[PDB]
Length: 322
Image (cartoon, rainbow, N blue to C red):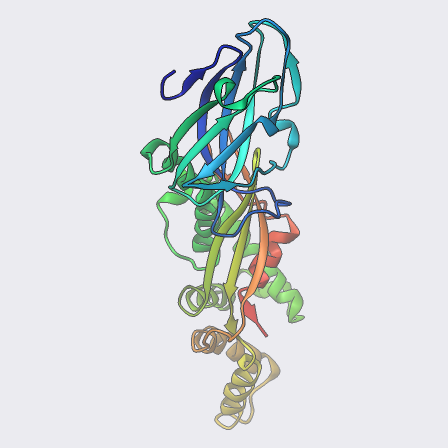
C-alpha cells in the first residue's frame, strides 16, 4: 500500500494516470459546469484463481458523495469486462462525472467470494493537484484556436499567436477569405466581376471587419473532444444590419439631391463608397446564434478550421443579421 499503488491478497491496483476530460457529445449524466475524471488503472491478479475485472468494480466519491460513472464517446476507450488468471493484468480507463478540483476517492472491490472490506482497496485523488488541473486547461485549446481564426479573418485583428496555435499561415488564409468574400459580394449584388480588384471592394471588406471587431461578439466554448477532432460551440452576437439597406438608399438619395445628372455608374460607385462608413455605424443585434464548429488537431497539438466545411460558412454568416 502507497499513494497510487495498493493491494489486497487477491488483487493489485495501480493508478497509471488521472486527468479531466470533457463529456461525450452523447453524455446525458453531466452538467455544463461538470467534467469527466479519466482514471487509467491496471489490475494485477495477485491471487491463485482467475479474477473477473469490470468497470462496475470501481466507484468514485467526491467529498462524501458517490459520483456517476460515465462512458466516453467510443466505449472501446474504457476498461473492458474480462477475466485474468494468476499474475495476469488488465489495463484501461474509468470515467466519472465530477465537479473540477475536488477531493476524490476511488474504491475497487474485486469480483470475489466473501467480505468486501478486506479484499477492497481505496485511493485518494487530489483534484486541486497542479498536474491534474493542467489537463482541464488544455480542454478549451480548440476554442482558443477558433477565436484566433475569427480574430484574423472576421475582425481583421492581429494575433501573433495565430500561427503557433493553429498551424495555418494567416496571410494565405486571410487573402483567400477576402477574395472569396469579394467574389461572393459581387455575385450576391449582381455587379460586374470588374469591381473584384478595386479600392471600393477592399474598403468594403476592411470596413465590415472593423465593424465586426467592435460591434459584434463571439463566445467560444469547446463542448466535446473525440480523438483528433473537437466541437466548439460559438455563440455569436451579430451586427444588426437590418437598416443598412435604407442607410445606403438614404445616402444615395442625398447624392441625387446633390447632383441630379448622376448616372447609374456614378451612383453605384458612390453607394459602394458609403457602405463601409455606414456599416461601421451599426450596433449589435438583440439576439444571439449558436453555431457548432468542428476543429481538427494535428501532431504538434494545433487546432484547425476547414474553410470549405459548411459549418465554417454558417459561423461567418452568423456575424451579420439582416
